[PDB]
Amino acid sequence: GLEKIGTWDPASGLNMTESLIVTTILEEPYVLFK
Image (cartoon, rainbow, N blue to C red; front, side):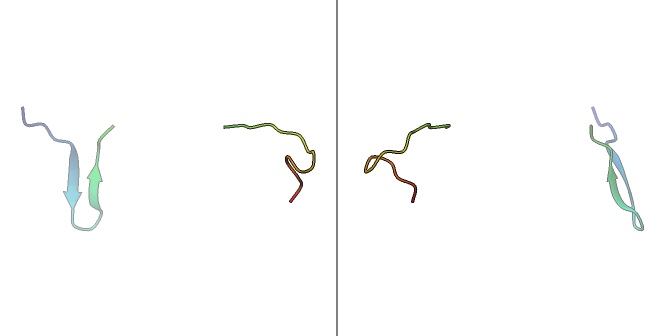
């Protein structure tokens, strides 16, 4: 049915009460430190 969920009041606003790792090795020219 219709149940409350939160309160408005124009000062405080709307208090809404809802609750890949890839390994390699270094060998030229396969993989090099850039």
